Amino acid sequence: YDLTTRIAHFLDRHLVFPLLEFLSVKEIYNEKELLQGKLDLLSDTNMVDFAMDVYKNLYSDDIPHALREKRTTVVAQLKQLQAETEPIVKMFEDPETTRQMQSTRDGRMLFDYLADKHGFRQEYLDTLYRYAKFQYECGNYSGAAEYLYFFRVLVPATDRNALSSLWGKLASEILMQNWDAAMEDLTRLKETIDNNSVSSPLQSLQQRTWLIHWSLFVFFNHPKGRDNIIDLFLYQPQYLNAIQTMCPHILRYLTTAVITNKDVRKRRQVLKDLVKVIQQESYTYKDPITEFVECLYVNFDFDGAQKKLRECESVLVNDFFLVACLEDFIENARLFIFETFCRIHQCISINMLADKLNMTPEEAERWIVNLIRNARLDAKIDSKLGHVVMGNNAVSPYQQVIEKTKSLSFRSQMLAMNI
Amino acid sequence: IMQNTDPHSQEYVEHLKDEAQVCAIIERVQRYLEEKGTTEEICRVYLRRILHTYYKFDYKAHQRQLTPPEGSSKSEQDQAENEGEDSAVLMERLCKYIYAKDRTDRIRTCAILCHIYHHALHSRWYQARDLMLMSHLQDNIQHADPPVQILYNRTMVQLGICAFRQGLTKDAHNALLDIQSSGRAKELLGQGLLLRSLQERNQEQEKVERRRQVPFHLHINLELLECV
Amino acid sequence: AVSGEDTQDRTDRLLLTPWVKFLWESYRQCLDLLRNNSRVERLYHDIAQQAFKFCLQYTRKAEFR
């Protein structure tokens, strides 16, 4: 793109907080885990995706990341280390600091009430300066941070603070599982990145990565935000023109949000502009699932397709990333290919179909009869065999032109006939 | 020297025996250097370094990669050479910040259009289209002069030839059709006839372009181009 | 190796091709100005047949002219 002549000088030097280290030396399947090598960097700390991992396969490598956070609550970190039976003798600095925060707080908490009480701007803005200073120090006063950014988000340096603060809030309130407060930053961060301060390529790209995470936890059916992320900026597989960015799930969850909520007539716009472009060419070399999902599909394979599609669904059910719609993908991954395979077909067996997807032929029959009920194919079952038949040759296209080509001219000659 | 002897003759090959010796001189400008370190403006010598490796062809680029990779010697005395085409990405990236010193568009833009020719032969076809379609240089090189435009037209034809070498006939046709829109390829090499129709009427400018064209052994073959 | 020819022409252009151009130019100078029946006598036909044999013995490029 036109920004990418600029991105090509900077060569992937993004403003990460954790400095490239992760839960390293992993055992199990990698394109699932590799997302915590781009998130847990561009998206700062991503600690719910540490707690998720142990439940499928035990680690003690979540522990070094679990030492190093304070805005969730300081002492929750101070326990997980003790639980791993670690001497960590010199924890004398967070008890020093986070205590003396209560002494500092009794000023701002007093000033805060008295100002919003009076309705007096000056006493509220000097508070907002004292209080936007403070609410990055500890987040356990969650109601105080919530009350702070409620009335005024315009602080003494406006957009600079507001961005790192609404981002620090969108980050911390997902870690509190305060999804309603994170849904407040869903409104406010997406405007703050669009009304941009400087548009420097080091931050412009990172701000477009931050557009993922408010859609991602699925407490209140947020994936409808597919319709937002296609309108807010132009279409891209990754919203970063630096190809060194890689999210697998952004396209899997886009594929879920297209099919499971809207009509399949809407999916070949994606198959062009999001499944073939220059970023996605690098992506097609790498991810197994999302490759099988579309490359096998668009080639109109059926044999390797509906087998390796059915194989993806073993790796899908291994997902402990929080979503509501993991199974409506498993549903539609069988539906969508079947319609397209049978589209030009002669005669498919319900029995061959049922051997493949590991269902009984009765299920496959009522499934096919429901695909025909839904009128996604015009077909008819050879009931004796348990085979299903499409057979439109549709000869004689001549008549399609013949009515209108005269009905046009007979009513359009009326124009020149008038005067 | 190399522009001014007949290429169809023995003397041309006898004068190519110096093309290693110019590299043996400029490669010495690394171990013995005092200017301000390596990063003030001396970095010119390692644009001059790549100007003898940017073209080097598919067979030669695989001499350490497919011709026996494990058979050659492996000391620090050898590894300075065995870095090979990795020096051709080290010298793509490290000093862009220092070349940003020059406001001259007609020098600033030129480097990327040599650099893509590295990836196109020394690696995968995608990594050439990558650095091209990041950069959007066509409207800028139409503001730049003919000796920069040589690199745009030279590199764009390889993005089509590599598409055919991968078998993607559509994107091969998309890239090659621009150059093949007219019988201009001999004048894009800088070697056109003073007359070949009833049109040709310039003569003051022709001797400027005969001084400003590429040497023989860096020509890609035209029968090959037309077959591809 | 992308554009370099095998060495046989490379030695024959050094030592032979001026002489094949001299034979072409020698046959081309007399059977135009002098030798042909644009006049009325000395028959050229012993010589006129040999230039085609020369195209086969040496280089085909002269036949078109």
Image (cartoon, grey):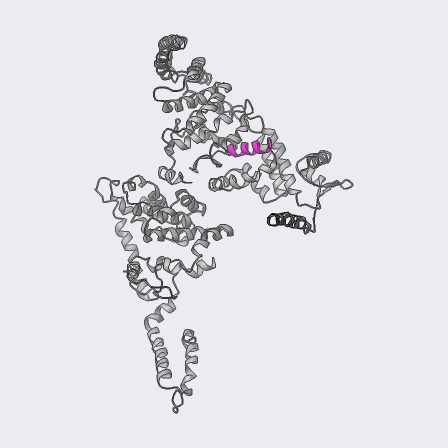
Q: Residue C12: percent from the left, percent from the top?
A: 36, 71
Compare residues A395 and A318 and report the one nearer the observer. Answer: A395
Q: Residue C33: percent from the left, percent from the top?
A: 35, 83
Is A31 left or right of A20, judged from the image as shown?
right
Above or below B158: residue A330: above
Which residue in the rendered view is the most extreme toward the front? A419
Q: Is residue C45 magenta?
A: no
| Residue at 45%, 48% in the rendered image | B125
Magenta stretch: dominant secondary structure: helix
Q: Residue A12: percent from the left, percent from the top?
A: 39, 35
Above or below B209: residue A182: above
Compare residues C18 and B122 and report the one nearer the observer. Answer: C18
Is B104 left or right of A220, judged from the image as shown?
left
Compare residues A122 and A412 and report the one nearer the observer. Answer: A412
The magenta stretch is A250-262
For the N terminus of chain A, give its image quadrant.
top left
Q: Is residue B84 shown to the viewer in this render?
A: no
Q: Is residue B75 shown to the viewer in this render?
A: yes
Is C21 left or right of A362, judged from the image as shown?
left
| Residue at 70%, 48% in the rendered image | A394
Q: Quadrant of residue B130?
A: top left
| Residue at 37%, 19% in the rendered image | A155
